Image 1 (tube, each protein chain N blue to C red):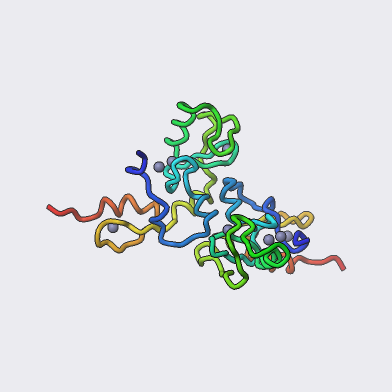
Image 2 (image 1 turned 90 degrees about the vertical axis):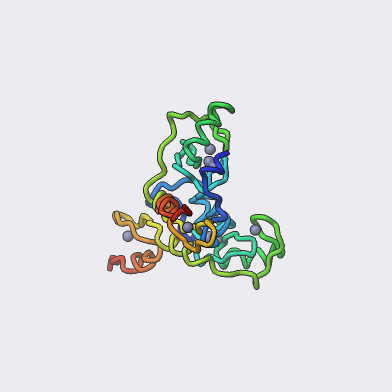
Length: 116
Length: 116
Ligand SMILES: [Zn+2]
Ligand SMILES: [Zn+2]
Ligand SMILES: [Zn+2]
Ligand SMILES: [Zn+2]
Ligand SMILES: [Zn+2]
Ligand SMILES: [Zn+2]
Ligand SMILES: [Zn+2]
Ligand SMILES: [Zn+2]
C-alpha cells in the first residue's frame, strides 16, 4: 500500500488537537498528506490517492460526495503548504532520536549512514 | 451572543482548506477560537463556550460526547497556539484595507483613529 511510501501521523513530534491532525491528513489513506491537492470542495488528498478513487470509484469527492474531476485538482494555498511542510516528525530509524521537518525528512532518511 | 466578542472565520485573509479552517474554529460557537482550551479528548472550544455547555448541558464533550469536566480543560500545545495566533485576518472596519495577525488584532482595532 501507500504505507510503504507515506508517513503515519503517529510520527508527529508534537501532540496536536485531533481536528488539526485531521486537517493535515489525506482523507482517503489517512497518512500525512504527500503531494496534497485540493478539490473544488476544499478537501485534501495525496495526488495519487484521489486520482485512483476518481477512476475506480467514480467522479465524486470521497469526503463529501460532490462531483469531482482530475481537472479540478489544484495545489493547496501557500500558507497551508507552509504549515504542513514544517511539521516536526520523529524519525523511526533504530536508535536515531532525531526530529526533522516534513520537507527535510527525505533528505534525513537518505543521509542516514548505512551498515556496510 | 459571543459574536459581539468573537471573530468570524470569513475574516480570514487566506482561503484555507475546509478541514484546516475547522481545526482553528470553536466546535460550539464556530468562531475563530478565542482563548482555546483542549478537552481530554483533544477537541477545541473557547474557554467560555465550553464551560457554559458543561454547566447547562452536562458533563460531556459537545464534539464526541465523552465525559468532560472543567478541571480537564488545558491549553493547546504551543505549536498549535503559534499557528492560530499567526492567522492573517482582514479588518472589516469601513475603508480600512488592512490585514493583521490574530495576536495583533485587538491592538489594531484599538489603535483605529476615531471620528471626534
Ligand atoms: Zn498513504
Ligand atoms: Zn493519501
Ligand atoms: Zn469534498
Ligand atoms: Zn533518523
Ligand atoms: Zn463565539
Ligand atoms: Zn466558542
Ligand atoms: Zn470530544
Ligand atoms: Zn482596520
